[PDB]
Image (cartoon, rainbow, N blue to C red; front, side):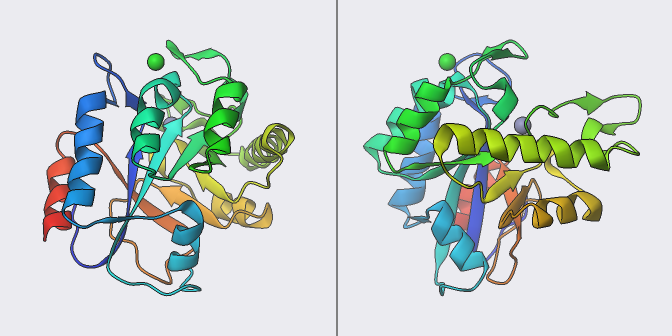
Length: 233
Ligand SMILES: [Cl-]
Ligand SMILES: [Zn+2]
């Protein structure tokens, strides 16, 4: 996690929970947001981020976009009140086919709960596949990057966008790769299906002219000092 200079850093959170893996505590989460704001970081909307990275609106200074991956209930139960009380926008990348279910041991937000967050004007929902968030340990890569799977990826993506449109009544501009990475083949499928931004877990400071690709910092105990130092600097 190497971060220097003015530009857009995009944070990737998953769960806001007290005892789980890939989770940050409610208290710690709020303290992180507070610290960033305290030292002068500007929190940006997904639309602002797109116009910034596309250099279509113009700059300046130190920018941050908050994002969450998967659809965990804790985003509604614990993250959302923190965000709402601070009026901080965020992008929620959901596994559209796992919404309203238990997924890998965790309750997911329901559609009612996602809708309520969208209604606040703070939450924009993106797609995190429909139901292709699976890892192949034999091949050491995600199922959607396995050979001969480009068709399956295209169909899943189209299903995901259709599903979000049906529930939220909105075209889906934003996509996040499960496990953080794609190929030129999958990038192109996303482009032709109308996505304006494609988010990865490449930890970098994003600058105007980087669109459509956005590097995100996965927030961990080890990566936070780097973001905080970058912010304070
Ligand atoms: Cl929860
Ligand atoms: Zn994920």
